[PDB]
Image: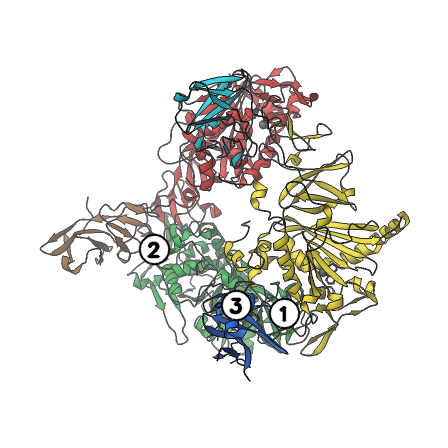
Chain colours: A brown, B cyan, C blue, D red, E yellow, F green
Amino acid sequence: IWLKVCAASDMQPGTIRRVNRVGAAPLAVYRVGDQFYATEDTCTHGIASLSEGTLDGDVIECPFHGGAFNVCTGMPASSPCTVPLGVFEVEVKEGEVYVAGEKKL
Amino acid sequence: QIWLKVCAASDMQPGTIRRVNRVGAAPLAVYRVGDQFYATEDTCTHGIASLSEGTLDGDVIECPFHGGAFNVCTGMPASSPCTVPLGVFEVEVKEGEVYVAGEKKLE
Amino acid sequence: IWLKVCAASDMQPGTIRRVNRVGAAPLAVYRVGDQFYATEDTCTHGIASLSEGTLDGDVIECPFHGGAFNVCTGMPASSPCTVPLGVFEVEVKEGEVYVAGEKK
Amino acid sequence: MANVDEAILKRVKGWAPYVDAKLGFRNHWYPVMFSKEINEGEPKTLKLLGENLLVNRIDGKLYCLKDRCLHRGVQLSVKVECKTKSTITCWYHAWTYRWEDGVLCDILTNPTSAQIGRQKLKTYPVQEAKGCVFIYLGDGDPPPLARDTPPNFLDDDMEILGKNQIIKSNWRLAVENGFDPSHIYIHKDSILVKDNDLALPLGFAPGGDRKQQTRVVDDDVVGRKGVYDLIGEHGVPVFEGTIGGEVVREGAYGEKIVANDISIWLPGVLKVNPFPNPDMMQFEWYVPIDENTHYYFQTLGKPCANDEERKKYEQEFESKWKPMALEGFNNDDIWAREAMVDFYADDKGWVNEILFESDEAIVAWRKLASEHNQGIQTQAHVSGLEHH
Amino acid sequence: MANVDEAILKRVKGWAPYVDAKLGFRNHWYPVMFSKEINEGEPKTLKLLGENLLVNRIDGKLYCLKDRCLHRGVQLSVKVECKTKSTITCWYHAWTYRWEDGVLCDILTNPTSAQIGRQKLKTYPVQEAKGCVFIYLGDGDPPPLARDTPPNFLDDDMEILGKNQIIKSNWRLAVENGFDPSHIYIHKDSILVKDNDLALPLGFAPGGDRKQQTRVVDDDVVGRKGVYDLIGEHGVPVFEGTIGGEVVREGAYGEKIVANDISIWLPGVLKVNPFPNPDMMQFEWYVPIDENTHYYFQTLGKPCANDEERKKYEQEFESKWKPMALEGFNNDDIWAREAMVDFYADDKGWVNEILFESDEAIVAWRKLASEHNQGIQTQAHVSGLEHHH
Amino acid sequence: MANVDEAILKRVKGWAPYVDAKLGFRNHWYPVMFSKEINEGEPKTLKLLGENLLVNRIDGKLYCLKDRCLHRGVQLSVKVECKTKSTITCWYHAWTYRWEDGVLCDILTNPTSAQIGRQKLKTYPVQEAKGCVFIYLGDGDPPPLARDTPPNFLDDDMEILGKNQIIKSNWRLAVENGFDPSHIYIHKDSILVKDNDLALPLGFAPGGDRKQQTRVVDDDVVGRKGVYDLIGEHGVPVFEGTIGGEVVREGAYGEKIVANDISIWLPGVLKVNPFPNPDMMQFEWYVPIDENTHYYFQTLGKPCANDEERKKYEQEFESKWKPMALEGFNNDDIWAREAMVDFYADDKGWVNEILFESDEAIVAWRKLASEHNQGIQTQAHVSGLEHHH
Ligand SMILES: c1ccc2c(c1)[nH]c1ccccc12
Ligand SMILES: c1ccc2c(c1)[nH]c1ccccc12
Ligand code: FES
Ligand code: FES
Ligand code: FES
Ligand code: FES
Ligand code: FES
Ligand code: FES
Ligand SMILES: [Fe+2]
Ligand SMILES: [Fe+2]
Ligand SMILES: [Fe+2]
């Protein structure tokens, strides 16, 4: 049900990490200080990889057009984005970070 | 009709404006700049606006329609689009009572 | 060879003096502080006289279009000037300003 | 929402929103054509409030989609491809949208695309009433149509007929030409005056009780918002024009009394009652197309209890009303609007205009529109909303 | 004032006002038409310095009113309604003004309006001289017309005839093309050269003494300000054009000597003497209509002592001078002006131009104009002057 | 450099330089006409990257000068005056330039001017290859032409034939449409598909990863920069278009397989191989003229070992390939490009576009273009580069 991403130690606060999932679309895990979050890697406004964007607090900015999303809620934060992002549950069990195989309900 | 009774000098705080409606004649505007009183026609010369509904900035009244303005003491235009001088009416206080002339100054 | 131009003191700091030469293009001598420099006088972008321009540090600004040159290297400092100015070495000896006879 | 230089908006404190609304007011209904002009399965194009739209009739019902593909921004109308009754396929990369909800349901160039079912093309509510096509150029479920229509336009017995065309002037210049009491001076030679034996003064001057002549409506049960200029009941009919005391022109001393009352209503529709005949009414819209143009949507209403009357009216309209009134009378309004373009084109006319007494009603309208409009259309609404 | 990007204006320190005067100089007299083109009660429209104007002749006298109703800013000329001999009524709401002082004297739609007698439409002085109509596009009492006319234009016996048209180029490009000693190269094949046996070089190059060829006039008693380019007496006629030392073109070796001296005067009028004949003079104005266009007001003057001579000159003007000179010679000046539009259109040409010696006269003009003009016409003058207290 | 709102450029981090390159990329070779279009001593005008240029053929060799006199900025072409075989003289004040190096060698109106030999009119390298005229719109010594041409275009046995015209769309819209894997849908009804029995799908259902969708070439022996469209390598061709599971359209089931090889190269030239027939190739340029227009320079290449084959090919070209392919097929590309103008005209489409899978090809090009172009042409290059110390 869950996937092993990395150790909380490997990620510095404010960094991003792309999670490739063979057979399915890629995910993006963001470390906002001490809390980890995960959403679809693909920007809902196109075909850009959010993991290649810029993270400012709990907001991720797409590299293609500057659209943005709240990595916690998945909701659009900056135009041109209008379609919410698919958010996936994350959990840190014993220093390591895990991400649910399917997006939360 | 020479002098029109407006109100007690007390009924007006510094930097305020009061409209004086006259029977059979155009309205006037009495302005209190500090402890001094001045008066002009109430209708902006650039249109049909009521200057008494405008903003008083020291001794300059700004029309609410287009932002034009006049010096309340001389009646001369202070801000565009106003170009026609306002008619000025003498004001005097007799025993704490404000009075405004019924006729404007000539020149 | 050298051309005796003037006495160092004949020029106030930050001023420019035009030096005419019979049968040759006029030159401009600049006094930057207590240092002296020389270049062709005609702006390379037209017919303007740089000696009637504005001196800012070691850069002379043409009065016509605002183009400019570094009076030391002669290289353009501001558009529309593109053709380098001719530079002439200068030497001050005994309070007298001398400028090279030919560009160098 | 920032369409005009801020220095100017700061100057017109009484109605800055109105001056800023160069593209019109968003979130209001607007008539753009007549029902008879749009047939089943034949998509039609038009621009409203700067936006390119496509209207189609499917099973008798109208649907409106923004005429701009989500992909590369081309107009679908360049080459219409309606492959199934309920959809339209962009001619470029075949992105396919449903007319009913605008959802991107298929993409022929890539049936596996992750965009399918995850993007939506903008749709706008469309309603037909009195043979007129109304489009709600706004967001969210629409308010009732009556809110944006003048009183009586929707009466069951009211038979509506009219014409529409594109005029080159901002919609506001049209509005202020129409709701103007003194502008009828330009209609003193219209063939309608003589030919219909109308009683028409050169101009309706302001009577003695101003607050009685102008009536601001903001208590209408349906939510209508507008202003009345009660010229006939409070204004003064000026029939003899003078210069230096000498009569130089006279109004028309006909027997037909018309234009008893005139009213302007958001989003910008004028009602003239009664006109062009004592037993009729005129309802005309000045619909914003872009900042330089508007639709001059003219309608004439006349009660009709039966077809025989509807036909008789239908004949009088084609043979007299339309030719003599809608055109013979109003054509002069067209170039009049055009004539004000230059003064207001740079937005500075809104500051330099020198108004007089009869403009009192127009001023009331500017304030009412500023206070009660449902939104300012901006160029960003046209290109795509922007925000950080 | 602020018609051009400040960064550019700061660069042209020698003549910023001139470069900024894209709309022309306010407070100067400008010819706009000939007297015979405006008859009694025949209102005529025209744009001068960017302002729409209406001119009318009442009892023989000319009057000029701004063609823009004070009310909603429409042009009164869309539908002229001169209800009475002394007034004009706007076709819109009937505001009525007096041609004599522009006073709003009546309002047919509201006879009791308080605006009546309390508003005034802008008026401009108009004056006829030598069959030409001059409008003083300025404020306050105008100066004598003489100040804005070239010497001799107003002489008692000087008979003036001409032609006028609208040319698509800014007025300054016209001025500089006219007061340009080297541009006559474009006229080497003009039919006037051969057909009038003119002696004309390919160009007048700078003489030996510059300050001697150019004469800045600012001490003229009538107040006129201008610059002379003494090409004939101080310049060098170049008759053999060479490339690599080889002769590829020669000027004209006719007997008639013309263009001894040329001078440009504010607000922008050129005087070529003598031209196009040894016994004639040419006076031409480049009047600013807007930033992209100007009136090319051409006049040819020739002394005439009586009607017989005046009529004789008129016949010659129509049969020879107009078609052979005004058109045959100056038509090339028209497309020459148009050819410089793109370069200066963005105002960048005033910085990127690469001038040579013969342009020294033009440079002198730029300075004189910048220093002695009577005001810079701005867009605000057109829309309505602005100012915050 | 800075042709677009800075707020937009800041948003397009993946390819800001490309979005900024409104006017095209400077320092690259561009085809502008065919050799047969310019004859000996007959100068021709054209605009490239917004610059007006003049091309002449002298002693069989081509020379290019900027069509703008240094003096007052007029186009020399308004009235061409080539007075000696090696020069061109401005029609205005006779400044004369050498076609060889653009040096101001003479001034007929002032032979002793100090400007002579002290100024230089901009010149650009010009090279003829495959019957096409290429101009290096750049500064300094030009690189080999092969750097800016697709592989095989310069092959010794490659016979090149083509057509050129001006199209109303920014050059980038033309490039992206040409390299767009899914734009094939607009060609479904082309006469070429039917008359040449071509197999043509409606599009492709992508297969494999993103990196596999294209092949970027960052360096060729000659420094070429380009991208290959590999969508068909692991992608599934779509021959039956469905809507709601219902078949509403079908691709073309012809037996001729073409376009197995599609690549776009800087400065903006597409290579489709083989096309329009299994034994030939298509190389087409989208040359920037100004911000709203480009040259659609089409060429078809076919190896030919002798003069007979070249003759036959030429006959095939004029009788079939030109009308059926170049026009019959690519005409739809022309209006497709025009259809995207409005959305990108305000530069906002670069932000609001909603791309899908096949656009990976376009994205790869935007990045390659952004990373390897040799310079951004700016409006300043057109009027005159600007810089204040
Ligand atoms: C006053 C009187 C009549 C009218 C008007 C104002 N505005 C109008 C607009 C259309 C038709 C008639 C009128
Ligand atoms: C030199 C020589 C003659 C003329 C000139 C400059 N500029 C002119 C303008 C009009 C008519 C003649 C001339
Ligand atoms: S693809 Fe992310 S904002 Fe457009
Ligand atoms: S009505 Fe007062 S400034 Fe216009
Ligand atoms: S003449 Fe010096 S910058 Fe132009
Ligand atoms: S632009 Fe419509 S499907 Fe691509
Ligand atoms: S616009 Fe002239 S009277 Fe109203
Ligand atoms: S503009 Fe070419 S020589 Fe003067
Ligand atoms: Fe009307
Ligand atoms: Fe000339
Ligand atoms: Fe194509």
Chain letter of disc 2 in the image: A
* Same subunit, tags 2 and 3: no
Q: Is mark 2 within 8 Å of ligand 3?
A: yes
Q: CA distance from mark 2 to mark 3?
A: 40 Å
Q: Residue at x 55, y 59 (%)?
A: E13
Image location (x, y in percent) of residue D261: 53, 19
- Are the residues flagged by discs 3 and 1 in contact, CB closer than 8 Å? no
Report the residue that reaches farthest toward the right.
E308
* Element type at mark 2: loop
Amino acid marked by disc 3 = Cys
Amino acid marked by disc 1 = Pro
Horizontally, residue F55 falls left or right of residue C57, namely right
Horizontally, residue E175 falls left or right of residue E160, namely left
Horizontally, residue B104 falls left or right of residue D253, namely left
Image location (x, y in percent) of residue D169: 55, 37
Kindly identify which numbered label has been placed on residue E88: none
Amino acid marked by disc 2 = Phe
Quickly name the residue at label 3. C81
Q: CA distance from mark 3 to mark 1?
A: 29 Å
Quickly name the residue at label 2. A64
Kindly identify which numbered label has been placed on residue F43: 1
Q: Residue at x 54, y 53 (%)?
A: E4
Question: For residue E197, what is the image quadrant?
Answer: bottom right
Q: Residue at x 33, y 64 (%)?
A: F233
* Element type at mark 3: loop
Q: Is mark 3 within 8 Å of ligand 5?
A: yes
